[PDB]
Image: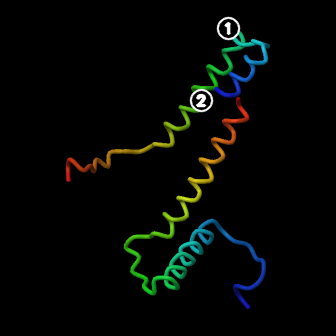
Amino acid sequence: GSGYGLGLSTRTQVTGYQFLARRTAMALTRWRVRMEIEPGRRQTLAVVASVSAALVICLGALLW
Amino acid sequence: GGMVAMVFASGSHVFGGIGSIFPLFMMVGIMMMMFRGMGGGQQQMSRPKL
């Protein structure tokens, strides 16, 4: 049937899936879907900032 | 800057005049791309206006 297998895809479908993925992930831990504020995003970005800061210092050592 | 500095510590000192024109002109291109990045405007919302 439709939707199965490795067919083609578009850039609006890629972001569309990430929205549904966030909204369902929130329902498993907070049991509500109002989502006036979206903390999953922020807790993830804090890790990406942590990794980036580690790499900046790492390259700083190689420069010296 | 790191790429430029690393060459001086090696002593090749190829920069100055003829050589410096590349990093000098190359530096402008980066700023020109960030300027297009902040593109648009006229929204004019601000804490002091609200």
Q: Is the residue at mark 2 from the same chain as the one at mark 1?
A: yes
Residue at the farthest top position? B17
Task: From the top left corner, tell me how far across and down residue B4 is, in percent.
Answer: 69, 22
* Mark pair 2, 1: CA separation: 19 Å
Dot 1: within a 10 Å radius of its alpha carbon, few (fewer than 14), some, or many (20 or more) residues?
few
Quarter of the image with the N terminus of chain A in it: bottom right
Provide the chain ID for the residue under circle 2.
B
Lateral position of residue B35 relative to residue B5, left or right: left
Query: As rendered, which of A61 and B46 lies closer to the eye?
Result: A61
Task: From the top left corner, tell me how far across and down residue A6 is, in percent.
Answer: 78, 77
Lateral position of residue B35 relative to residue A61, left or right: left
Q: Which mark is residue B29?
A: 2
* Residue at 52%, 85% in the rendered image: A28
* Residue at 42%, 85% in the rendered image: A32
Quarter of the image with the C terminus of chain A in it: top right
| SS at circle 2 | helix
* Residue at 71%, 13% in the rendered image: B15
Q: Quadrant of residue B26?
A: top right
Query: As rendered, which of B40 and A49 lies closer to the eye?
Result: A49
Per the image, the residue denoted by label 1 is: B17
Q: Please name the colour scheme applied to the rendered image.
A: rainbow
Q: Earlier in the sequence, mark 2 or mark 1?
A: 1
